[PDB]
Every structure is written in C-alpha cells, then in structure tokens.
Image (cartoon, rainbow, N blue to C red; front, side, top):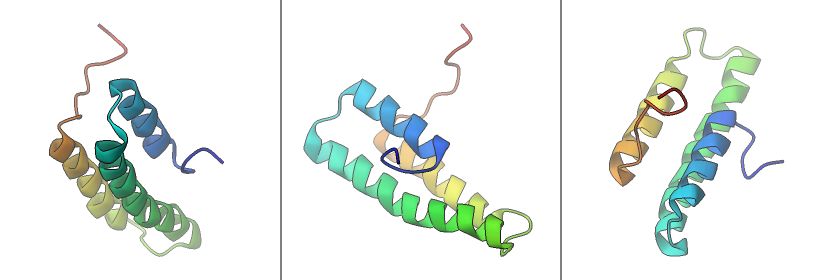
Length: 82
C-alpha cells in the first residue's frame, strides 16, 4: 500500500520528501517516479509472470531510474555506512 509497492521506489520517495522537494518539483519527481512505477510494477509483474528472464526490462527501467536520479540530481550511494 505504500505510495508504490516497490521498495526501490518507496525508498527513493521517502528520500525525496527527505530532501523536501516542493509539490511542483515533487510532482515532477513523484509523477515520473510513478510513471517509472507503472513500468517498474509492470516489471515486478514481468519477472513474476516470466516475461524477462534476464531482467533487462528491469535494466532499461533501472537505467530509467538511474537517469531519473541523474535528472533531478538526487543519486549518491555512499549513504548508511560512513
């Protein structure tokens, strides 16, 4: 039930709100995140129904998430540990 049903998206969403992005720019990253959510969820359903056996459709998606983050400029990776 969380905004989306994919941990990656939820995790990223919580992160954005953490950056506190205004609604407008948050609709941009939230909306796109959703679009990617329709394709990402359609993916979780892909790998579930057995449509992509190598997860490429996940690849393109991930590359679309990566880009999404490189687009808003909210990537990073050296978190948690420090």
